[PDB]
Amino acid sequence: MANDTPFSALWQRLLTRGWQPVEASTVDDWIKRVGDGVILLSSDPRRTPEVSDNPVMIAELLREFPQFDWQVAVADLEQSEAIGDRFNVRRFPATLVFTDGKLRGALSGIHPWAELLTLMRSIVDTPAAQETVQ
Image (cartoon, helix red, strand yellow):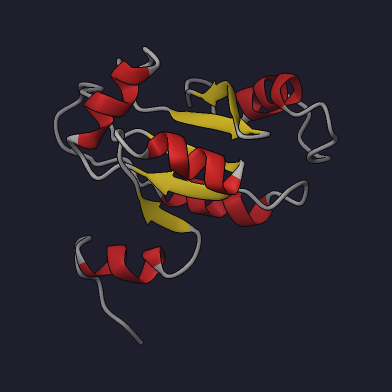
C-alpha cells in the first residue's frame, strides 16, 4: 500500500486536511478570516548538513490537540523570510501562534514537547492537554 516518494506528492495529500501554504502580504487577512490558527515558518538554516526535519510532527500535534480546532498554515520556502521579518522572528524554524486573531506566542521546538506545556499555557490559559508533565 502506497510507496516512499521523497516529499513532493505528499504535499498535495497533506494539503487536503489542515495544511495550507500561505504568504506574507496576505497573512493579515488570513488571520483575520479564521481568527484561530498558526503560521509555520519555513526552516531557516539550522545547520547540520542533510537530514531534513519532518514537519509531520506539527500535523501530529494538530490532531492530538483536544483543546481547540486551529488551522496549520505553512510557508513554502521564500515566504518564510517575509513572514518572519514582518514580526521579527526569522532566525530559526518556528511556528507562530495566532489566537483570537492576534499573535500572542510562538512554538520554537528547542525543548521537545516540554515547551508545548509551558509556552502554550501562557498563550491559551484554557486547559489544553493532560499528560507527560515535563
